[PDB]
Image (cartoon, coloured by chain):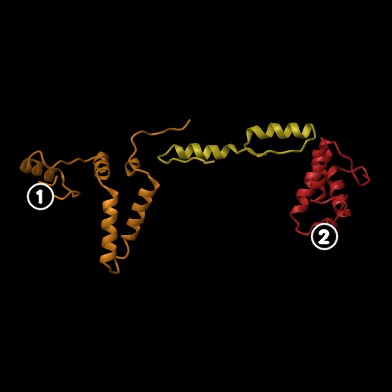
Amino acid sequence: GGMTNLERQQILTEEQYLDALEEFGDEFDAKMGAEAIQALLKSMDLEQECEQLREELNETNSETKRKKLTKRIKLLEAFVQSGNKPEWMILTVLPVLP
Amino acid sequence: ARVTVQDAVEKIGNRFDLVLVAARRARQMQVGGKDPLVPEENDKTTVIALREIEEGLINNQILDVRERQEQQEQ
Amino acid sequence: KSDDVNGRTKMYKNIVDGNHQMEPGMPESFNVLLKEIRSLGINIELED
């Protein structure tokens, strides 16, 4: 929901979500389940985020900016290079033992 | 039986190939088709093979030669 | 002497025939490990 004045990934409690839906109407969609996280991660292009993180690391340099960002880039590189789609982290079907 | 295995070690030196050579000799000795070149004293195949490698009459080389010998003689 | 089900019988036969030959095969506990790992959301397999 970009039309409404709300962040893409922000907390909106029950009363808050109620009043937001009452005011903005059926535009600021929200979910409260694991499927919410699944939708958040599936509709997210990894190459663009990787380029943005690389640009941020190259441009902005600080004691705290040097860390907490390179590991994110490494995780993104591992995900794209391994080919494992991150939606596979949230499992749908569950195996059981013989 | 043998108390110390040193003559075979000196004949080999690497200390790792001697076990392989003696094992590959003993396997063919026990399966049959060959005769002990050293006179036996009522002992198992492994001791006979190790005494043979200690005597300096068998190694990792002449086995290949004799094996190619019967392989081409077929 | 391990969980190799297809090895204990064959070693027994090699002894009684005096063969004294061993083929390793694969321990069954490794298959147990593979099966229990695949019980969770983690693929695992052995290539060639």
Tell whether C18 sits left or right of A79: right
Secondary-structure class at tag 1: loop
Residue C3 image-quadrant placement? top right
Disc 1 target residue: A5
Per the rendering, the colour in which chain B appears is: red
Amino acid type of the residue that numbered disc 1 sits on in the rendered structure: Asn
Per the rendering, the colour in which chain C appears is: yellow
Disc 2 target residue: B10
Tell whether A27 sits left or right of A88: left
Whether callout 1 and callout 2 share a subunit is answered no
Secondary-structure class at tag 2: helix
Residue C38 image-quadrant placement? top left
Q: Where's residue C26, x and y in %?
A: 61, 38
Residue at position x 78%, y 49% in the image: B21
| C47, B41: nearer the viewer | C47
Q: Where's residue A85, x and y in %?
A: 34, 43
Q: Which chain is orange?
A: A
Give the Cα separation between the discs numbered 1 and 2: 87 Å
